[PDB]
Length: 425
Ligand SMILES: [Cl-]
Image (cartoon, rainbow, N blue to C red; front, side):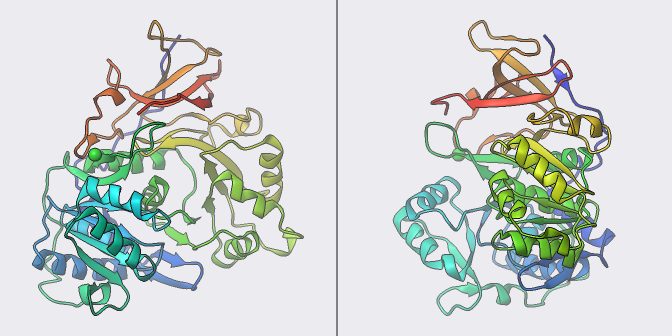
């Protein structure tokens, strides 16, 4: 019986705000490509992103936004959707994303949790947001990504004014909340998961030391999901390029890998079947591709194998994580290269600077390998708590996060998740 412990690293982003992080990354990697819209074939540099976000921030400041405010976003991925998020982060404000595919009743509840001062919304989700605010009986400024007479527009927020040259992100308390997500326990309604500047930056930094290639990474998930936000943070960290597309299609994804020379892609297992059913894949030059990132539901060994055949120069990395703490287990590309072709279907090994234990609930004691129990985890990437609710029971007597998952580990420390505990809040 032991506690699995990931490899050490020296944190470099543990003394600053998330806004200062993003700002510094922009300066460092100014001439590199920050983001590419795979659908429209448009791109933008870190330099340009810095300019537009600085202008949005200065305007947000004039509207009275400070670090205590929550700024909300409801939009699919575009070249604009992250700009006001970055801008809001410069001011130390709390940022949170809503899923445009959620019902009015679900959005209403989410808004009631975080009661935002401003919400940026895509044109397609404007009625949804208007209806939800009306239902929740909440007042909130709406700013549209597009045209509006009734509400303000994103284009207005990018209007240059003020001392752009002198602007610096606000000094703030790095243990204050920087980013929020929403819980999904097996019972009870969602709650607002709070990450501090420190905790979120450790989600990002821990993912970097997992060692996987992100130089040019494609994804489809919106910023509602931890993966969306974590990928953005991770690409900023070393001046890599984030690529997005609205919908996953097999053919178009292979075309994008060829067209942009992608090194990586994140997507849930079930969509990978669209890749493996593309006929005559050899007609695409996929030689740039190094890493298919996946997880969240189980992947069959045959599909796993088919994927390695489709991408012969790549590794397939199936990981495990959650909104409350980021990435928890995954195989290191080089250090675990041998096991990546052997030990399917595990979730990999524990991530750097992370502790993972399996606990027998009755008796409440940690167990050895090949003994199933409740997965519990602990690291500096852990959420600080809920925004207005009580996360006390999410953590055990030793301060470990209860994942709500049942699993076990190997003699070689490979992790296996098998099921969720029923009716856990
Ligand atoms: Cl809450």
